Image (cartoon, coloured by chain):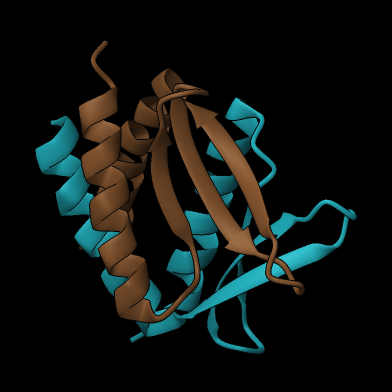
Chain colours: A cyan, B brown
Amino acid sequence: DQYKPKLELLSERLNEEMKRIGTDINFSYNDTIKGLVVSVKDANGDKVIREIPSKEAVELMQRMRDVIGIIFD
Amino acid sequence: DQYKPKLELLSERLNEEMKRIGTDINFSYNDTIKGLVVSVKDANGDKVIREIPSKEAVELMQRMRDVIGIIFD
């Protein structure tokens, strides 16, 4: 499938939500490693990152949608 | 206003999911700071932590369901 546009969009929305709250957590789509990248800065101000390749990320966002549904809806 | 049990379930299910992807991101509800604790290990094995207060975490989760809803299917 085409995973770039949607994970890009999902990132902007996630980041807006994170900045609405004041939590230093960043999301973005990396087109080089083909995945979602979440990043936080550690105690020294240096980036620590976690990558989740495109396909695993879309499945995960879907499973979380339904979990969030039953828990909060 | 009873945020604790929903955040605990969320953390629990979120953790199973992170473990499924083999990504290192831990979620938990903290009684003490009354909210969500997310953690990742830095280079030296030390947990970097971000905390999202109970109410705003529920908010975050709630409206993340929606955008995921729109973006996926």
In which quadrant of the rendered view does residue B61 lie? top left
Image side of residue B62 versus residue B48, left or right: left
- Residue at point 44%, 81% (across, down): A54
In which quadrant of the rendered view does residue B7 lie? top left
Q: Would you say residue A63 is visible in this rendering? A: yes
- Residue at point 35%, 45% (across, down): B67
Horizontal and vertical percent position of residue B34: 45, 22
Image side of residue A32 versus residue B58, left or right: right
Please, is residue A28 above or below residue B9 in the view?
Answer: below
Q: Would you say residue B70 is visible in this rendering? A: no
- Residue at point 86%, 62% (across, down): A46
Q: Nearer the viewer, residue A8 or B21?
A: B21
Number of labels in the image equals 0
Give the position of the C terminus of chain B as an image quadrant: bottom left
Image side of residue A26 versus residue A65, left or right: right
Horizontal and vertical percent position of residue B1: 26, 10
Horizontal and vertical percent position of residue A31: 62, 83
Extreme residue in the top direction:
B1
- Residue at point 21%, 43% (across, down): B9
Horizontal and vertical percent position of residue B21: 36, 79
